[PDB]
Length: 275
Length: 10
Length: 100
Image (tube, rainbow over the protein chains, first blue to last red):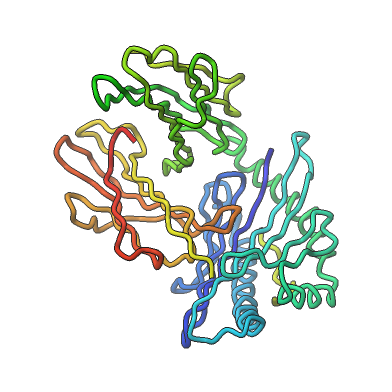
């Protein structure tokens, strides 16, 4: 129903040069903050209007936390290289994602924290937020180190407390946009390949949030096998786009219906090519 | 806001 | 070392109408590692001032970026996205098609 998520990417650079630390924060599908250690004088920066007037202390607090995170990740990246017997000549990637979800009732549903090394699962907090699952023997070292300081309790405290409190404050500050779904604007276009065949492309435009289902049916039967379904993509203005296309014989376009389900629609839509 | 980076290195 | 080659989509923010200002997008996704080079092309020539979103990634750890520039499409002008990545032997080029 609603969520706040942070995403960390730490990339070591070979031999000399410290790593590149980038963090972004999201409420649902809206980014609100970015931090890039490569900046001139790097600091947390607003990426959404509803955090811009939070005041300098808020932003000095975030910036200091970001900077300390980047220093931590630099040691972490050296530790990880040692766990896997990796030389300094190579670039490696440490990723972390954590956040909290609210349910339909507006209240805490789950917390999560997940880490990956070179694009593969490394270690994850279990959903009870009280222990970890390690993907390999290296990650079991990390787990033991985190257990030594009993770090699950502070993650739980943050995820079930600070994360939820601040998610609800961001959701209030940005109620005008964050709590208003934008229904997809939908239409069907017609593209001949020959006089005997045409592509029917069903469009969904300007919607929010990103979650959507687009489907072609032929005489009411699901044409999942013959459907070219493009991945949902950002329009660049905070809304999203998707289309689904099917190749039909000429003269039979009316047997084909497109179906779109979305949060901003009170019930699934049904449309067909209108020549 | 960010989780305070008092959690440990990997 | 997971290597994932980028998926590419090139498209306009609003339906293209010749002569009206708009935005040309190149959404690169599904790739790993995150080093990537992305240019927008006009008639095969690099567009100079292109902006891009902040590095983020999906549930399966692969990264995505949006590159974008203001543009005013015409009936004659062609546009493309050109992407380079360690998984690619040569830069991959996807032409803009206003019906896609």
